Length: 257
Ligand SMILES: NS(=O)(=O)c1ccc(CNc2nc[nH]c(=O)c2[N+](=O)[O-])cc1
Ligand SMILES: NS(=O)(=O)c1ccc(CNc2nc[nH]c(=O)c2[N+](=O)[O-])cc1
Ligand SMILES: [Zn+2]
Image (cartoon, rainbow, N blue to C red; front, side, top):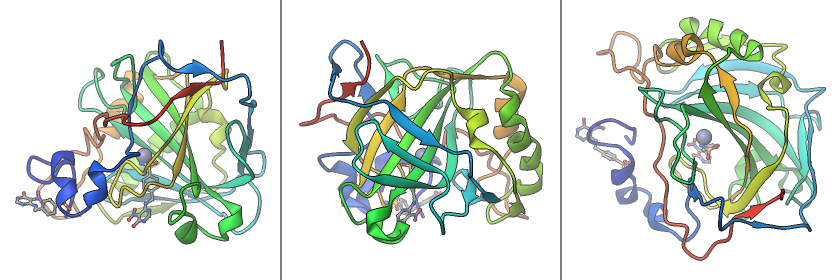
């Protein structure tokens, strides 16, 4: 199986998922100087007031906080998007050290982690159908730097010891993802892909300029998670990020400045 270990990491994925070397792969380096301001972009609309979290799962690659997406409750719209995208889950990618961990980079700068709020286009009826379409998903990307704690993150951090190993899940209700957003919704956007296999080219990426601050103790707790299942040799869950991929024939647009 693919992973991020010594022998099955990102440079190996193409052998099972040939679209790894495709025309619209993610993440990418965001060259701030060459991203053009696009005054036709709209403000992003993040409507998470009715979000219903249900569960948190260690899937052996990251942990996902899953939402009830059976009704139009936590939606992302506007920005570069046409139509309405419903929140299904969020997860993070992070490093073994504070100097690395994000998937997207900003003029080659790597952040300590990166949060992905994953949304699917309601015109496709469900997630599984949406990932088959070029405009199927919108992922809202938010950088994490180490500094002041993020109080809105602590409930997530505190449950991780209950889902240490691959395939563990825990009840995770009433979590409000608004506590994870920075103050500004200024963003960059570009057409890309899932950053893990199956690496489908179905994502409008929206990457916020303003990172959120999390404490060293918070990100330390992410690094105590395990890639392995229970009663297998311990492999800390760290460096679960794909490096920047060739931008190819794509423009990154800025909503600002
Ligand atoms: N193209 S892909 O899906 O990324 C993929 C890549 C590599 C494999 C073989 N994996 C391994 N082979 C040898 N030793 C190991 O320790 C692992 N391992 O770590 O799994 C299987 C699938
Ligand atoms: N890192 S990211 O780009 O935000 C991101 C990556 C993967 C997903 C959903 N995963 C899947 N999607 C479709 N088919 C699949 O088979 C899987 N799967 O097997 O996981 C959602 C978001
Ligand atoms: Zn992700």
